[PDB]
Image 1 (cartoon, rainbow over the protein chains, first blue to last red):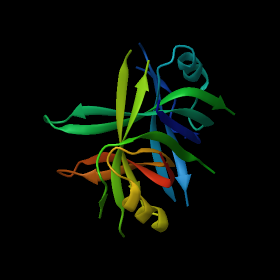
Image 2: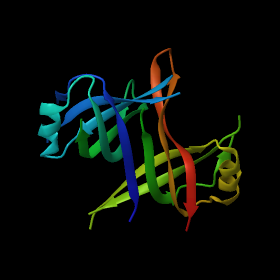
Image 3: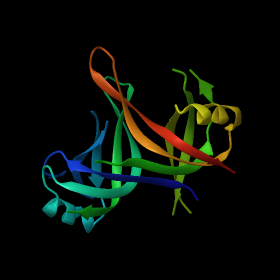
Image 4: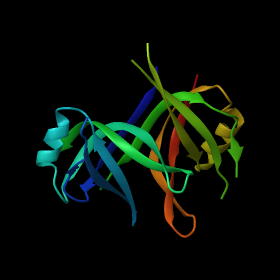
Length: 92
Length: 95
């Protein structure tokens, strides 16, 4: 076995979007300003609708998941879309 | 106040490399379910004691646990802003 775990607690940028559907929204995380923006995806079949329904613009949550390294093309070379795939979400 | 912390435990892919200096190696994480899937991470250490400890010790093939934060490296090409993800690490523990 391996481990690939992430924990994030921050404010959501915008209302979620639904794009094997998938809820996609972003998340800000601060240092002291450094702000780090995360691309969040939820594929899981329950939390997926929960997080669509109830996660909103500017809301503060905690999530756990795993990082997933997407990898796409711009003109035939190999560029990096980095996503955080969430297994669990904790709402305020 | 926020929170960006990550935990990974995996095999190192090649002997590390040094480069405000920084040590840089790569980790593999395997998800199994018999099927397999591997995720390759760009690890980078700053903190000064850890950094030379990793460098002296972390070697191609080692099983290692660590923790750190996510950093989406922003760089540019033909002046379009792109990304290199790195996992910037606060600590490691060896097998």
